[PDB]
Length: 304
Length: 306
Length: 8
Ligand SMILES: Nc1ncnc2c1ncn2[C@@H]1O[C@H](COP(=O)(O)OP(=O)(O)O)[C@@H](O)[C@H]1O
Ligand SMILES: Nc1ncnc2c1ncn2[C@@H]1O[C@H](COP(=O)(O)OP(=O)(O)O)[C@@H](O)[C@H]1O
Ligand SMILES: N[C@@H]1CON=C1OP(=O)(O)O
Ligand SMILES: N[C@@H]1CON=C1OP(=O)(O)O
Ligand SMILES: [Mg+2]
Ligand SMILES: [Mg+2]
Ligand SMILES: [Mg+2]
Ligand SMILES: [Mg+2]
Image 1: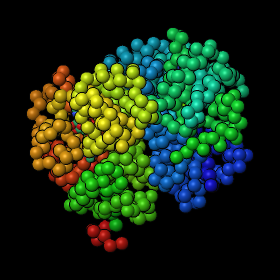
Image 2: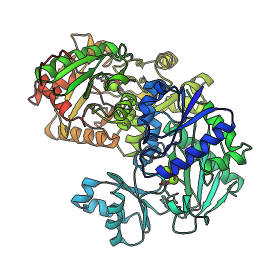
Image 3: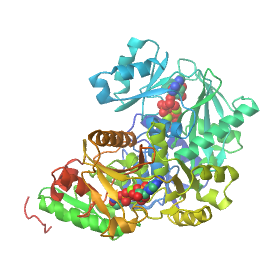
Image 4: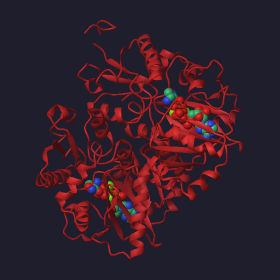
């Protein structure tokens, strides 16, 4: 079979995606698969089956490639594709609705307030200001539907919030204000029915931002995560429940942080994770005894 | 040389026959409004070809998976064709009753107590914790597939020993099923059109619940619009429905189903992002009470598209 | 194409 490896696209994470797709391609060609890079910014994707491919590997990040739109197109084109279906992809991109779903399911999530742009440009009511104040300081402000820490700022003073919302609202119509979690920070990869070894992330700097993710050499990673056996077990159980509640499939990565109470809190699910080498999914597969090439082969194998 | 509109109807879901009827009425209604609309059935026509066929915009009159669950919306977004109703995420969520319920509960909105089961769990055999949770709902219960419509796959369980039969039926239609506390009713439905909440409708089936026969075939189902609620009860219902619609991220138009229970409280059942549009359907009924003919309604739904 | 509304 001929494989298309979708890379680049038109989101804020285009540059990361170009690097993931480059790495996925090579690992796939090293595995004996007939794979070829296709960039949706360059190539009309609606033409894939007419171009001669019969399976797709999605190495796109962000809205378009990760939010169910592509998965819907591909489902109707017929073509099997890597990762989560339409619902779980769309839901996993929307951090507000992920949070609501997990809270509904009794899962641990950081206290938060959500705001729309219409609510912001009008001005905040006393009800909303009271809710925001009960979060304490500091808080994090993030767009609901971004990735790679885009549009995020940490606010440490109450009068600095309205400015941080202005930045976030340049990226989304819906914004989250969340309680600042102490850390430490972890990420857990999923592959089929297998939860892979957790990774602890220690950024130099305020949080795990875009620079810390892709540009800097100062970020420290620990695989395995160095947790006590009971804590590692609790982390894995929590991630499994989070994954299944969202309805995710195939592979992915869920972000989790400890807070000051010594408990884990779910941040988000990523359904088309980074695949450079700076990247965390390949690192966990390696620890489990898989080469990068073996990982991408397996991800392709679990499709519809 | 104005816009050519495709009315998608029929398709391959369990609700194909209802959708043929919805599309038939929508087609005539749009033409009555001066819109150059044509029927396209995805069962017979490759919808990946709509743009190449010369269509500019799409009225979705499909019901069920394949038309209402975000898959089609996804395709149309990449094709760059504007379409009616909710986008990819809200369509996918509204189709999934299990995840609609979780989201609504996360938002502090009222939902019937329930237990969810996967097909794997049912086949493994129900645990003692599961039988306990199910028993706590009391009897009767209602059993539904997570992702159907038109009461397909649903039934009422009146004896413990027949729960298995209701589950086997629902599992013929989905890989995830819900068992819900029985709500006393009465039953209502509330249509949404753009930023307007339309008059609620009280629904009174002649039989056990509002099943496929009561919805589409019986002349004994009774409807009341207006619903006969006291002014503040009506306001409360409309406020609940708006919050449920906004929580799911829905847009354009739709219809949310709600029931009272013995405690005097309203409980959300589900949202429908591509509701019935037969002549006798409930969205047209609510729009009629609000002063709109059927043609004025479909023209408005189309105007709301992207 | 032959249309339901001819012209436009
Ligand atoms: N509530 C929080 N408290 C502290 N740090 C946070 C919080 N939420 C996010 N972060 C930091 O921001 C980074 C990105 O946030 P995340 O929710 O994973 O969004 P993204 O999709 O941008 O990765 C996290 O990896 C973490 O370093
Ligand atoms: N918990 C419940 N208790 C009593 N009747 C219910 C309950 N849930 C649904 N019903 C009945 O079943 C019908 C269909 O259920 P609903 O959840 O609306 O699914 P559908 O998508 O098939 O319409 C309702 O219109 C109502 O008559
Ligand atoms: N979405 C980015 C791209 O690859 N992996 C990601 O994870 P995130 O930075 O969103 O946690
Ligand atoms: N899905 C059907 C067809 O159109 N309207 C509907 O509502 P439901 O029967 O799902 O409550
Ligand atoms: Mg992310
Ligand atoms: Mg993250
Ligand atoms: Mg329904
Ligand atoms: Mg219903």
